[PDB]
Length: 49
Length: 49
Length: 145
Length: 7
Image 1 (cartoon, rainbow over the protein chains, first blue to last red):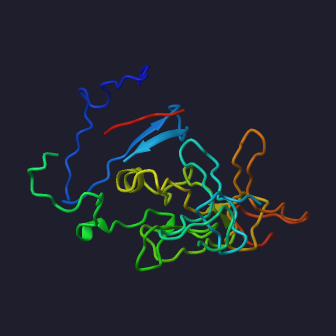
Image 2: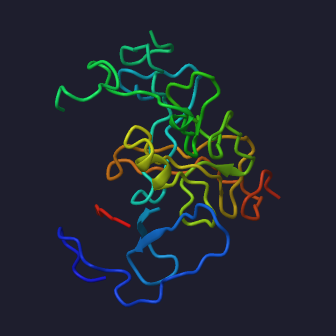
Image 3: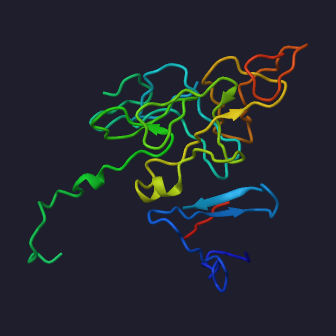
């Protein structure tokens, strides 16, 4: 991600391939998770479900 | 030993503040209880009034 | 808003428990034994809950109770279950058991990690023991070999 | 340290 700041940034799926076709019907819990560094595990800053 | 402020109560003895080793993710809390509605407590107390 | 609309109820009435959907279930880390259940009860130190729980389960020997972010599949309350349904009255509290590393051991059950409310002054630690000299422990164990 | 998110 870049800059961020107080203003919200149009991010995530702009022209990406994150679209997933589900199989079972029901309630699914999608989970965004932010990390400081790009190494496993790193530091999880926040996680909105 | 710390007294959590008014409007909670510890009936059981010797429960410590559950900790969190990575704070920026899960914030630590105190193990005293919301003092169920209809009852109040004046700072440290064993049973809500 | 208009004093010409059929009023649902009186004016002092702010909130109502309309239907069974209002009976939301507690997040992980809080148990609700009673039937009234006006406020959910934070599980006490060491004991660990699961979803909407009736009773807190004691954490096993050789384990304490801190966050579980490093570990896989932690039983932490999701942001959905607290912020969206309740708000700020029930924040996310740690809920899982951690194994103390090699060369330390926990004989007793349900001693959680003591916390500190200011970090830069006094650091928090874990309540497992130096494993008396002449003995070792293979990661999480209850008795030093 | 503080991060507001939406999804």
